[PDB]
Length: 142
Picture 1 (cartoon, rainbow, N blue to C red):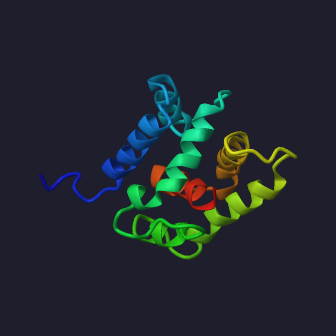
Picture 2: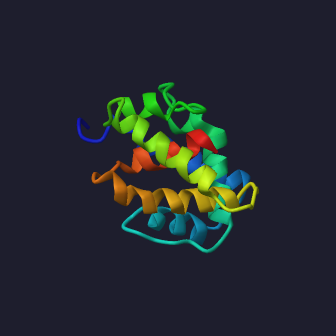
């Protein structure tokens, strides 16, 4: 129907489902993930971070149109709801948080730190990035 047929929503969910399978992430971690960005939630598991680095291995599954790539969240933002300022702001949150991150260089835990930091810094934007814009950024950098 001419309703929800122009949205990366499904393809996102497929890349998540691939991580839910290829990593066998539990439905509780999947639900925890979807709750994470939903208002303001702190996860304390590590498997959600492992999901994030897997979504990041699957940018070609997240946006099969060809926007989402390494360091390339800008095109992905542009085709959704940003311009070069907004699309750079988010890059600067992850590029900020990734360096401000503690001495723990890990596959899942560092992702979690930089991702929770990112949501804290969504406060300083004084706008509200789309679910797309949030999750696509961590993916592009991880």
